[PDB]
């Protein structure tokens, strides 16, 4: 069965690293039937980030590339 079921209702904002301290990606083949990026705000709220939007694509690129430089 599906472990979890990703957020079926997304958001329409431009959230930033400015507000993000966490991130959980949801695919349509791991459990959910749809795919939603979960950006965890510094406000303890899970944002249903649309995989459709570039600000999301941008943040998820950085969130996948946490290379330890500093």
Image: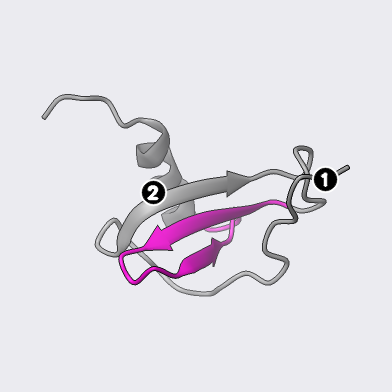
Residue on which disc 1 sits = 2
Q: Residue at x 39, y 68 (%)?
A: 44
Q: Residue 1, how many percent across, how many down?
A: 88, 42
**Label 1: element kind:** loop
Q: Which residue is mark 2?
A: 59
Instruction: Say which residue appears at 75% left-offset and 38% top-offset.
Output: 30
Render colour scheme: one colour
Instruction: Please say whether residue 38 is one of the residues in the magenta stretch.
Output: yes
Q: Earlier in the sequence, mark 2 or mark 1?
A: 1
Asked which secondary structure carries label 2, the reply is: helix
Residue 42 within the magenta-colored segment of the rendering: yes
Does 42 appear above or below 52?
below
Image position, residue 61 (x, y; %):
41, 38
Against 20, residue 31 (above or below) is: above
The image quadrant that residue 52 belongs to is: bottom right
Q: Is residue 23 left or right of residue 7?
A: left
Q: CA distance from mark 2 to mark 1?
A: 26 Å
Quadrant in which the C terminus is drawn: top left
Q: Nearer the viewer, residue 46 or 51?
A: 46
Image quadrant in which you'd find residue 15: bottom left
Query: Which residue is nearer to you in this view: 4 or 67?
Result: 4
User: What are the residue bounds of the magenta stretch?
Assistant: 35-53
Q: Residue at x 53, y 58 (%)?
A: 53
């Amino acid at each position: 069965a599906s472990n979890f079921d990703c957020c079926l209702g997304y958001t329409d904002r431009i959230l930033h690293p400015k507000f993000i301290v966490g991130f959980t990606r949801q695919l349509a083949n791991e459990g959910c039937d749809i795919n939603a990026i979960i950006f965890h705000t510094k406000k303890k709220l899970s944002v249903c980030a649309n995989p459709k939007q570039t600000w999301v694509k941008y943040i998820v690129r950085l969130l996948s590339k946490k290379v330890k430089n500093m």
